[PDB]
Image (cartoon, rainbow, N blue to C red; front, side, top):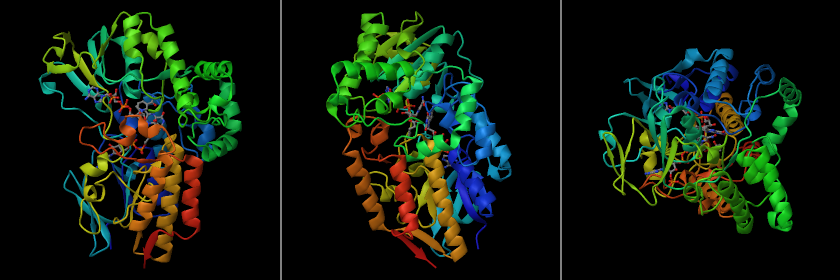
Length: 529
Ligand SMILES: Cc1cc2nc3c(=O)[nH]c(=O)nc-3n(C[C@H](O)[C@H](O)[C@H](O)COP(=O)(O)OP(=O)(O)OC[C@H]3O[C@@H](n4cnc5c(N)ncnc54)[C@H](O)[C@@H]3O)c2cc1C
Ligand SMILES: NC(=O)c1ccc[n+]([C@@H]2O[C@H](COP(=O)([O-])OP(=O)(O)OC[C@H]3O[C@@H](n4cnc5c(N)ncnc54)[C@H](OP(=O)(O)O)[C@@H]3O)[C@@H](O)[C@H]2O)c1
Ligand SMILES: CCCCCC(=O)O
């Protein structure tokens, strides 16, 4: 008989909600282990300047509690890291969840014990305990990726990853270097350029970026949104990307050149990178002329905004508009600042980090006090592979994932009885809170069913999982997304497999898949009594 009914790993959006359901709704004995010193997951760790979410604030939140929806106010269109952290803290208080969240506790081992049919979980702290159900809410974008750049550890000043931003660090008036220009890099750069004495950008691959449209909320708009929240959430849940806008059904090449320009301009003026990729035309990410047209539209704005022709050239990507789409408050305009310098690593690669800065292949030592790694994450599977996580057959999860990470439905794993993942591999690529709520609710129901019916294990079959791999691959091969090199398909860490790691059918379709599996009696699962 186990120490706990369930153990949940992680105290981000995922685990907070998981806990709430397993404890407050099902009345189970549950504990959460979180390695951080406080709850919030992403929004605990990512304390860097400019950290914020690109999901517009009205839908970057839970939806399951209608009271909370209507009581909580947000004051700017998009939510800053501190505003989201404060929200997740308020949820934690609201639901009396802190008492079952054990902070500072890294789970190092999770071992299915076939004798007892229980999960045995070990912490860095040398606690081992048993639970019937394990839920892993480890975060898709949680495990910092810090490349082994030569000389990195010789750097004399403050060297930090964005995902480890120390609360004491004030970059005001300092000479700041940043490596990486994805969504983290670029929003850091915008905010950091207002603070630092000099900001040096080390850019390996330029990205496309559109305006965010960020700005203050009017209390009447907040009221309007809240009046209509039921409707708003219905739209979200039947949408593709769940960002609170209706995706376009217009093929981009089916209108005039003037119409393409106007639709793009209109989306540019309103802002949001997901709006620009999906609310403009329906085939930006499937049709290559449609994509090329979106991309050229962005290039023309770079060339207009950026006054130095050389900087504009270095900023202008030539590859597909098919990475996670960015937005920012005046990203390209930042490079007209006099305290910002752009180094292209295609032309002048980093040779060595040295005590006083970064020496590039040109021989130039860029002298710096702070070196910021916005070099992203061992995404999706990183925290799973770094855990001593072993299933029924005693094999480490790495031995099940030799071609890429796998699951059934993004939330279960063949060979891993009674384990459920929140934002596991091959789940939705959407505004994440509502995908999380879908997962959590679905897991709950199943755990509750095993409970009421006296099941001992629940496990997806090997065939069900391999069917889901097929599905995810086939959906991704109908898109351009696999032709974009990023973390989304792995390989952003040399030696990491290149592989499909998301269900790209969208939230509405992903919810339907979940509800079909439930409602048909969990075909694909072995339900042992
Ligand atoms: C800068 C930034 C901006 C983003 N903007 C958006 C956005 O606009 N829209 C959007 O949908 N998503 C965005 N995301 C993704 C974001 O991660 C999700 O929105 C959401 O916060 C995920 O919550 P989660 O609980 O699944 O994972 P996380 O919030 O990543 O929480 C996972 C937790 O698990 C803990 N943990 C991991 N492994 C272990 C272990 N072995 N033992 C113990 N604890 C462990 C971690 O320390 C972490 O606290 C953004 C991410 C970042 C980093
Ligand atoms: N605004 C938001 O809502 C927001 C903010 C931050 C993060 N996020 C989410 O988090 C995801 C990850 O974002 P991210 O920007 O943190 O990571 P990222 O998209 O993985 O970008 C990593 C950056 O570091 C660079 N890089 C990696 N290895 C390097 C090396 N060895 N040398 C030099 N440069 C290197 C990459 O260049 P290459 O492209 O050449 O590899 C890229 O510019 C986003 O895509 C998004 O989903 C969202
Ligand atoms: C896995 C990430 C899904 C999209 C939310 C984001 O880009 O932050």
